[PDB]
Length: 242
Ligand SMILES: [Zn+2]
Ligand SMILES: [Zn+2]
Ligand SMILES: [Zn+2]
Ligand SMILES: [Zn+2]
Image 1: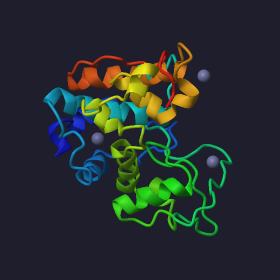
Image 2: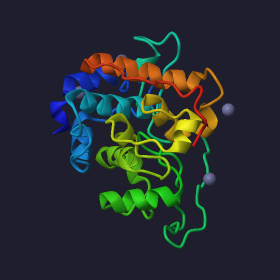
Image 3: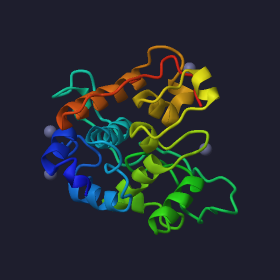
Image 4: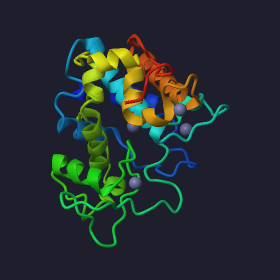
């Protein structure tokens, strides 16, 4: 039903050049896979006012677009037209396997970044796999070979809280109630705190940051496409990291 918020046409206008020959993931990410994945997380794009629902979709696609961007300053249609260009960590990467009796690593497998949110480590592939009913510890490559599974891992991240961090979904739909600690840290509801949730240790609270700006660029472009206002507190330049 997320299709009632974002049409196939709008989805492609947003992720405009993802299938250009220069992109590693060309041909991978499809609108039908996105819609199928969304069906497994009913609340996504279906919680709150029509505007909250549009921002929920735009923010999700904007943050994931930054994580997989292939854009550059003078890119065709701007740097914010190049999200979803990659589907797996570039380079030699690493094993990303840490001791865990709850989410044991499978021999010979590696848990490097895969998919829209660049899911990493066995302790994340484990709970994400359980959430979607797929054994991602034994078959982590499915996050880079099956687009529906790929999108599902990203939505799992979007919809899952990591207390004290709320889920990004809760923040964008206006369901997050900041603690006294959050208020003291300057973490107010908005797109900015979502960036903080995702990679605040490295990007937030130290003034202007090009990574934060790139995330906002995607968000504003996508909100413009769906026809919704951005909401407040878009940056995390002055927010203490979670
Ligand atoms: Zn299409
Ligand atoms: Zn193109
Ligand atoms: Zn690690
Ligand atoms: Zn810093």
